[PDB]
Amino acid sequence: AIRDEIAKNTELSYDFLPLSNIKALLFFNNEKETEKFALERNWPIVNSKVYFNTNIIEKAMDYAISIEN
Amino acid sequence: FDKFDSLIKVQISKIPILAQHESFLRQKICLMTLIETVFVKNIRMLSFEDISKATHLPKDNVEHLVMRAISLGLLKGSIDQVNELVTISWVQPRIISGDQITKMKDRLVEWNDQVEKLGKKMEARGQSIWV
Amino acid sequence: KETVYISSIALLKMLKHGRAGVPMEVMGLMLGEFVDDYTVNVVDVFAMPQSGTGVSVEAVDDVFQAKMMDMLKQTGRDQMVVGWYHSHPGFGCWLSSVDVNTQKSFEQLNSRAVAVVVDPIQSVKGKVVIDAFRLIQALIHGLNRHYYSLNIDYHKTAKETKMLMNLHKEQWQSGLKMYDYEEKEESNLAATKSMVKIAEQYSKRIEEEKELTEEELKTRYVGRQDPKKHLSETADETLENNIVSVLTAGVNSVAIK
Ligand SMILES: [Zn+2]
C-alpha cells in the first residue's frame, strides 16, 4: 500500500531513475524485485535506467450557433 | 534544361555567331528553368539545392542566379541564406504556349476542389444558423 | 494644429507624375488658398518640366509657369502658388539642404508656403507615404532642426465620392472582404478600454442601488443609460464583429491559398 504511492508519486516526480535508486526508494533488498515491480507498473526500462512516459473555422461557427440559439 | 543542352551541341558548331556567346545561352537557360520550376510550384519557395539540381548549377552561384533573375525584372522576392530558402513574391506574366496551360488547368482544378469541400462542408456545421 | 487639405485631383495628379518620373525625381507647383493661420488648402497642381540638374531653384521655370497661369485663368482656376511638390523616390520624406534653399526661395514669395514631398516607389497599395511641412529616418536631416512637419487631410465633395464609389463594384465580392485591420485594432482596443470604463459604473450602480431605493435611484440616473446596458450592449459588437472577423480570415486562408 505504500510502495505504489511512492511509485504513483515518482511517476510524476521525475522521468529518470537509475535502478539502484529505485531500490533505494521502494525499500527493496533486491535488484530484480525492482523490474518485477516496474513491469507490473509497465515501466519501460533502459539498462538500469527507467523512463516514466479541431479547425478554427469550426470553432467560429460553434461560437455563432451557440450565440444565436 | 537537358533537352536544350542536347540541342545546342549540334548547331553550336554550325553557326559561328552561336559559337560566341555560349555563356549567355547557358545563363539564359538556367534562368528560364528557374522561372518555370517556380511558376508551377504550388507554394512558391525553394531551397538552394532544388535550384541546383533543377538547373544543374553548383550551389554557390544559385544566389547569383536568383539575384540576376530579379535585376532583370523576372522575379520579385527575397533570399534567406541562413535557411537557404527563396520566397519569390511574384513571377512575371509571360505569354504561355499550349502545354504550359495544362498545368494551370490542373492547379486550378485543385483550387476548385478545395472550395468544393469547404463550401459544401460549411452548411452542415451551423445548419442551425442560416437566413 | 496647422493643417493642409489636399483635394483629390491634386493627390492623383501628384502620384501620377511621381510614379511616372521614376527613378528620377520630379517637381511641380501647388495651387490653393490660405484660409487662416491654421490652414492651407490645395485644390490644384501642375507639373514642372525636367532639368539637366536635379530639382532645384532654377528648375522652376518662369516662362512655363506664367504660361500655365494665364491658360488656367481662361479656365477660372486662378489661385496662389501655395507650395511645391517634389519627390524623393526610395529615400522617404525629408528635405535635403538643397531642398531647403529652394523652400526659402518660396518663403520670400509667401511666408506660409509649404513643401510637399511625395515618395513614389515605397508608397504602395497600402498606406501612401506623403509629407508636407516647412522650415524654421528624417531626424538625420534635422526633421525638427532646420524645419518642422505639418499635417494633411483630404477635401471630398459629395459628387466626387459618388464617382469614386462606382470604381469598385463590391456587390458580388462582399463577404470575402476583410476590412482594414489596424482600424479594428483601435476597435478591439478602445472597446475594451471602454468596457473597463463602464465596469466600475455598473459597480457603483450595484452598491448605491443596493443601499438606495429604486424610486430614489431613478431620480438620479434617468439622465444617462443603465450602465448594465453598456455591458450587455458593448460586449456584443466585440463578440460578433470579432467572430465574423475570425471566420472571414479562416475562410480566406484555406479557400484562397
Ligand atoms: Zn528633394
Image (cartoon, coloured by chain):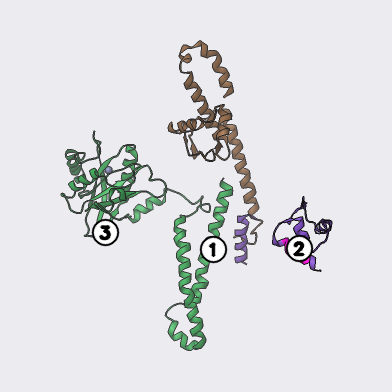
Q: Which chain is green?
A: C
**Circle 1: is it few (<14), some (14-19), or many (20+) Cα within 10 Å?**
some
| Three-letter code, disc 2 | Leu
Please tell me which residue is depicted at 32% across the width and 46% down the height of the picture: C118
Q: Is residue C193 magenta?
A: no
Residue at mark 1 shares a chain with residue at mark 3: yes
Q: Of C214 and C27, which appears nearest the observer?
A: C27
Q: Name the residue under label 3.
A: C2
On screen, C221 above or below C239? below
Q: Which chain carries label 3?
A: C
Q: Of B99 and C3, which appears nearest the observer?
A: C3
Q: Mark 2 points at which residue?
A: A25
Instruction: State the extent of the magenta-drawn residues as a range.
Output: A4-11
| Three-letter code, disc 1 | Glu
- Residue A59 spot, x, y in % from top left: 62, 59
Disc 2 versus disc 3: nearer the observer = 2
Q: Mark 1 points at which residue?
A: C240
Figure colour of chain B: brown
The quadrant in which the C terminus of chain A is found is bottom right
Figure colour of chain A: purple
